[PDB]
Amino acid sequence: GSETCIYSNWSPWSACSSSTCEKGKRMRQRMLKAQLDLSVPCPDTQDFQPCMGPGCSDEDG
């Protein structure tokens, strides 16, 4: 997980999959600085969290 891997600060998110107020997701990809285990790579280079397009908010959820 995040314990055996020491990565750089997360990259900025890409364009949100939903460019509208409809719930969607984003994509990111950081760089691995160091790993506590050289025999096991750190596949957590990328991540995905939900998003909402412009003119949207969490005022309803």
Image: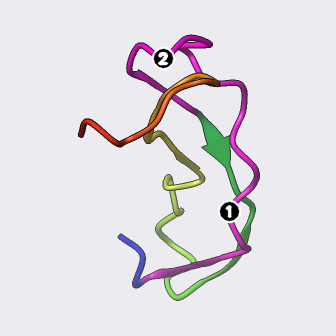
Residue 1 within the magenta-colored segment of the rendering = no
The residue drawn where x is 44% and y is 82% is: 4
Q: What residue range appears in magenta?
A: 4-26
Task: Considering the whole magenta stretch, tell me its main secondary structure.
Answer: loop
Residue located beneath label 2 in the image: 21
CA gap, disc 2 to disc 1?
24 Å
The image shows residue 20, relative to residue 10, as above or below, that is above
Tag shown at residue 10: 1
Q: Is residue 42 left or right of residue 14?
A: left
Q: Looking at the picture, tell me which residue is in the foreground, 60 or 36.
A: 60
Q: Looking at the picture, tell me which residue is in the foreground, 36 or 61.
A: 61
Residue furthest left as drawn:
61
Q: Looking at the picture, tell me which residue is in the foreground, 37 or 23.
A: 23
The residue drawn where x is 73% and y is 74% is: 8
Q: Is residue 19 left or right of residue 57?
A: right
The residue drawn where x is 75% and y is 50% is: 12
The image shows residue 38, relative to residue 32, as above or below, that is below
* Residue 3 figure quarter: bottom left
Number of residues whose C-alpha sits closer than 10 Å to that of mark 2, classed few (under 14), some (14–19) or many (20 or more): few
Q: Is residue 23 left or right of residue 45?
A: left
Mark 2 or 1 closer to N-term? Answer: 1
Position of the C terminus, as image quadrant, is top left
Residue 21 spot, x, y in % from top left: 48, 17
The image shows residue 30, relative to residue 55, as above or below, that is below
